Length: 230
Image 1 (cartoon, rainbow, N blue to C red):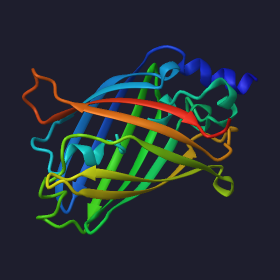
Image 2: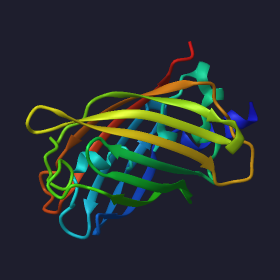
Image 3: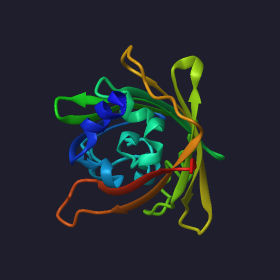
Image 4: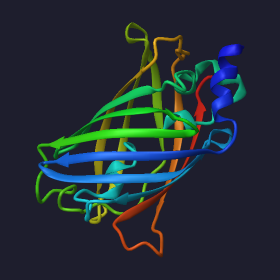
């Protein structure tokens, strides 16, 4: 299929990644840069994020989802369902609203596309209605991350997809902070794209710290595998 060929071909080996985020949550401004690489053959991402403006004013785990679905490993039997690669290299827009239960919400817009050999994810994040003393602005979330299925459906009238999912962030007192994710992606190009049957992405995320890093930062290891159409 010369369509599967084209997107396939962009992702076959290790691809460098650049992430840039401009953030304002309740007027607390911040910028993050990340760098790393993805190897979609294995569903594998390795990234390191740095807050370049100082202290990150929100917990690092709340930004994990925001900070590359094109790097998912789609099984051979599911390649006709891979919207994300099919949009490349022109890319796609990924927009979210994420509702933190009993607290504020993030609204994000990103463009994910190639700049030469580099896969780039440029993001604007606005958060509003946060509790200054809540779990987010009050930094009460543990520095860890749970595994989660993410449900993809076609958004035929917008030539794209919608994605819905819940993330439970562990709180330091032992409880959980729900983060309810609503997501839409649409191609940037005017070309054809693969529009998928309902299926899901299985995520595993491991957060760590660079022992030689003095800046406020997050190292993120993600494995992502498509499933749900046997």
